[PDB]
Image (cartoon, rainbow, N blue to C red):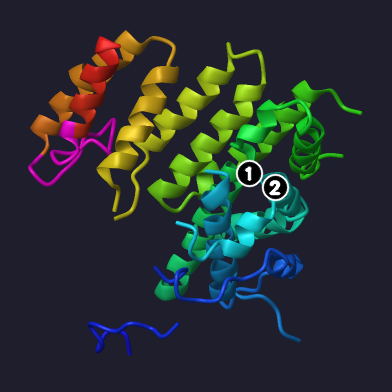
Amino acid sequence: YLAVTPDYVPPLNSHAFFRELDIEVFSILHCGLVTKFILVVQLGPPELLFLLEDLSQKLESMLTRNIGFSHLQQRSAQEIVHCVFQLLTPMCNHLENIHNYFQCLAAKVQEYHIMSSCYQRLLQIFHGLFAWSGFSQPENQNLLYSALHVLSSRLKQSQPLEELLSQSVHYLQNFHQSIPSFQCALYLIRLLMVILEKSTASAQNKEKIASLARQFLCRVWPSNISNDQLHALLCIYLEHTESILKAIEEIAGVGVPELINSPKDASSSTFPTLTRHTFVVFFRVMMAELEK
């Protein structure tokens, strides 16, 4: 009905018109996820996307105008972060199920996008929770330790903080092969950055960030990639690589000549994300990073 209705003012930007959902609604995320294909009343992909989209919007409002969030602003930021803390266990189960769903696709279309969108929403919520200004304070370090312990225990279960981050990043980095879209990869790589920022040792942390970032750049993403997202990933790869100068030689001295020899509607063999439409992004990042 909205398509055939150009101009219409709903009686009293969906958040400004729909009734706000309470923070206790997301307690039903404990229900398991059931997918019709490639796998009582149980949670489905379209219903999971609805809950995740609302939860991601709520966190983005405060952790990262007042219409549609009036009941949310009454609660404190710490309490909402505390509320999402108990949601880690159901989201990780949802996250793992989406991981397995995409892995089983190695061997319909409409349900594919919803599943990918759910996978995008979870990483945004995961990134938003850990990338909170409150974790810099010492009072919430116990909560941060508790949140990491949930992530670490997903593989094997008073551990020291260092291995808690090491296990959590390793568990999260295991999701890279199942990433279905460029946006999810950027959220995954940015989620690793904020968690690794807590660790004091950054000698090898930059290498795993840069190695994963290069793998995302060299991956043949099915066709969708925006220049702003590509610009963000290129900055991450260049700022974290071992030799920023040597990396610029590889892209400019190897990738660009390959693009020239390739036909007009093609891409570089070493960097499939580098095409004639994305050269401006690659050129702008390399020049700006070289100047820095």
Looking at the image, which residue is at 41% across and 48% down? 183
Instruction: Label 2, secondary structure: give it.
Output: helix
Quadrant of residue 231 within the rendered picture: top left
**Residue 167: % across, % down:** 73, 32
Residue beneath label 1, please? 129
- 252 shown above or below 36: above
**Residue 179: % across, % down:** 49, 49
Q: Earlier in the sequence, mark 1 or mark 2?
A: 2
Other-residue count near label 1 (Cα within 10 Å), few / some / many at <14 / 14–19 / ≥20: many
Looking at the image, which residue is at 19% across and 17% down? 253
Task: Give left or right: position of 49 versus 8.
Answer: right
Looking at the image, which residue is at 61% across and 33% down? 133
**Residue 98: % across, % down:** 59, 59
The magenta region covers 263-280
Q: Nearer the viewer, residue 75 or 128?
A: 75
Magenta span has 268? yes
- Is residue 123 visible in the rendered image? The answer is no
Exactly how many numbered labels are in the figure?
2
Residue 50, label in figure: none
Image quadrant for the N terminus?
bottom left
Majority secondary structure in the magenta region: loop
The kind of residue tagged 1 is Leu
Residue beneath label 2, please? 81
